[PDB]
Length: 114
Image 1: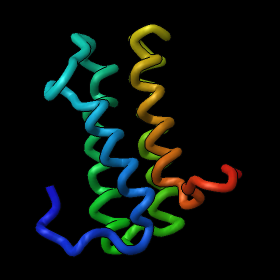
Image 2: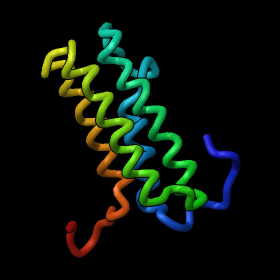
Image 3: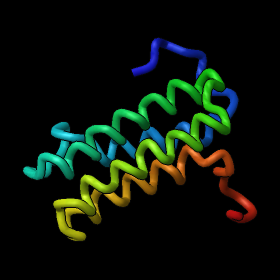
Image 4: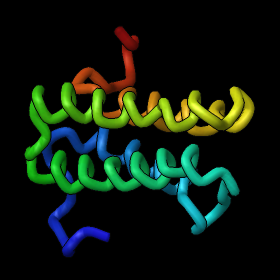
């Protein structure tokens, strides 16, 4: 829910992605996992993503931002690999990982992905 901007300029292509990430993975708004801890990740990450969007939109995201954002979300993964089983974790994993695939500076499409 931006504050009425004039569309994304820099790192826009990437932004669009983060948008679909949440639209597909939303706590309560769509699905939910009785698992308390394990869930603590879905709620956390999902929230962390939003920040990225607002950042990229104004070019606030930087090398460090991500580097740290990766360890901040990655670690959480434990909550899943801790209690929940690969089955329940599988869902989260996709997020924790995907998020890193979006924020990742190098994100584009066309000729090839590398």
